Amino acid sequence: MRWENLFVSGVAAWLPPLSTAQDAVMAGLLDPARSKLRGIESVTVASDAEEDAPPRMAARAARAALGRGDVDPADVSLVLHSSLWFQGIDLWPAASYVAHEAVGRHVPAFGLAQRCNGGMGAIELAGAYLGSGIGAGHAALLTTGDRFAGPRIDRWNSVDVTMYGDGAAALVLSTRDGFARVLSTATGVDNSLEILARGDEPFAPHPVEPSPVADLGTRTVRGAELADLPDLTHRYIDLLVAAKTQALEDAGTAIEDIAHAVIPVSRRGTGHELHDLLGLPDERTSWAYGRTTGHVGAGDQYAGLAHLVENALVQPGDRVLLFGGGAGYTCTAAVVEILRMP
Amino acid sequence: MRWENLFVSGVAAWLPPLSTAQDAVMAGLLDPARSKLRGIESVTVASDAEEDAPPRMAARAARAALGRGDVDPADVSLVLHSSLWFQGIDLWPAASYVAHEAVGRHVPAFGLAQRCNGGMGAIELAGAYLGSGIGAGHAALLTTGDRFAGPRIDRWNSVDVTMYGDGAAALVLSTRDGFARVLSTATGVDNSLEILARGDEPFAPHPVEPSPVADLGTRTVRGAELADLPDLTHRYIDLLVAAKTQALEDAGTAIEDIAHAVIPVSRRGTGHELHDLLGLPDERTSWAYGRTTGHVGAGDQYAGLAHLVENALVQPGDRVLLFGGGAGYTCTAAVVEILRMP
Ligand SMILES: [Cl-]
Ligand SMILES: [Cl-]
Ligand SMILES: [Cl-]
Ligand SMILES: [Cl-]
């Protein structure tokens, strides 16, 4: 999709303090070979206190993003809140809490689930909603938020390719103006890969209690066995290349013209990494930042953009690729252009 | 919102067998005073077999709906799957499963959370997406699906105003054509009422285990005490009347020209009900059907519309009000005009 009138007006992250891989190694929680392989140096870790519940971190992130962009909360016509895991109270609309705390009473709020791609997928849904004339205002607030906890989640081991960080992020879209123009978005998808995110886990009538420790790497092995696909790996590559290709083409841009790619925090640690498939070096991606936070649920792309902007690592005229990816498997990519620094 | 080119192509519900309130009373699960007061005769209850997990019931409801409007799977550009509760496997994209089974590999799929209003709210998000030009394809598949179970959910008691039904429903939207035209949608919302959905339940870092039985009626009582609002009931009335009036006005349709209203399944049983606020007799609402299914997650409006259509209880020219409502609190309403009987 080529966007004629879509802008990023604000972006921010609210992240708890860093907790080092070295401390996790010394405490016996993380094997040192895995620490070195995955290359994650630290992750963000929240306290157990109610004030660091995911909707609260999200509300804080949202207030900062709105504040950085001079978007009046009364101009927000939609709130989308993406997440991976428990929001702290069940049978309850988290997104309305985020919306109420950061925007107000009279804005429709949805919770969104597209695993790690949530943040990126929400751009397309919200952008479309803003262009439709359904809502009053010119802006949408997009949030992410998670806080991982035992026993179900072991942040250092429960997923093979990454390590989870706690926290929240926010991005404000506008059809009027902002510091960056959204030139394009594109989504690559291959829903056959969903089996890799459930492996042979049975469909249970109720959450299994007490929760065993999640091991998403292991689901992957039994998923691959069950799916029995000749081209399993190619299916991933093809959808990622589709997203990249269409987003760059719809932006009239080439990967050589991309100052920086903000990508999900994940690392194979040998062979080809995502930057190789994207066609740019490590140094032109957000890895140097993301390896200090870990995988902050659905928020890596928002957080990494905030990072670029806060540390004046881009200037007007630069183009940035925002690059998604989540179990499903779905990947939404966007090309933005820096118009001014906030 | 007035829609110039939005149609319902197909609608269907996949529902497990009914289970009577009468039997619940004899099994000691339901107080006879409560059964009498609420007027719900039966609720749909799925087996605990894996083939009745919510995403699988949803896939079947989807295939049924796609077949009824002759929408080619290849023309669906989005899938949205709304739900209230556990989908059977955690840390896993249930929407991609629904998408893969009903539609195919290359369609973006999102899970949606807006409690009981998710099925109606989805119509607005999907309609906007279809009008935006993001996808090739002129159709969207909207699904819902839930299957409630203990210990956490007691379908007969966990919510004061209704009793939960298991099952799934699907509604296929089109910008090209359909048997019904969506004349309008409108959303009323008041996010200050989110507190009524959490009561004084603290944010917990991890789901509480073992699960206590949920009691949403008690959350509403505690939440009202905590909020200390002067105009609690007026806030509900305002947002509901807002959704009704705009939906009606944007459809250019008077209340007395609504052939039927499909509403959420609930009942106060005191002689003042939702139908009174809407300005229609009980007999022109879906209560007679609803009270045999219970509250089928986010699917009451799809399910009720399919019931009307399958039993030829409406005819071309008839305008139907689909009326949402879910904790948040958000309510999306729509006026649909029957064009043909498929
Ligand atoms: Cl490893
Ligand atoms: Cl697991
Ligand atoms: Cl009662
Ligand atoms: Cl409760």
Image (tube, coloured by chain):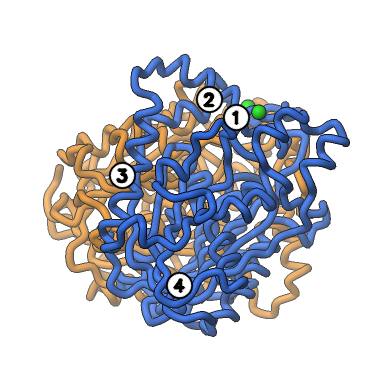
Chain colours: A orange, B blue
Residue shown at 59%/34% (left/top)?
Answer: B269
Label 2 resides on the chain identified as B
CA neighbours of label 1 inside 10 A, class few (<14), some (14 to 19), many (20+): many
The reply to whether discs 1 and 2 touch (Cβ–Cβ < 8 Å) is yes
Choose the circle earlier in sequence order: 3 or 2: 2
Q: Is the residue A142 above or below the residue B320 in the image?
A: above
Q: Is residue A80 left or right of residue A29?
A: left
Q: Nearer the viewer, residue B288 or A93?
A: B288
Q: Tell me which amino acid carries mark 4.
A: Val
Percent across and percent down for residue B222 are: 53, 18
Calculate the distance from the C-alpha at mark 4 to the C-alpha at mark 1.
33 Å
Q: Tell me which amino acid carries mark 3.
A: Ala
Question: Can you identify the residue that label 1 sits on?
Answer: B216
Calculate the distance from the C-alpha at mark 2 to the C-alpha at mark 4.
35 Å
**Foreground tag (3 vs 1):** 3
Choose the circle earlier in sequence order: 3 or 1: 1
Using the rendered image of the protein, determine whether residue A148 is visible from the camera's viewpoint.
Answer: no
Cβ of mark 3 under 8 A from ligand 3: no
Calculate the distance from the C-alpha at mark 3 to the C-alpha at mark 1.
25 Å
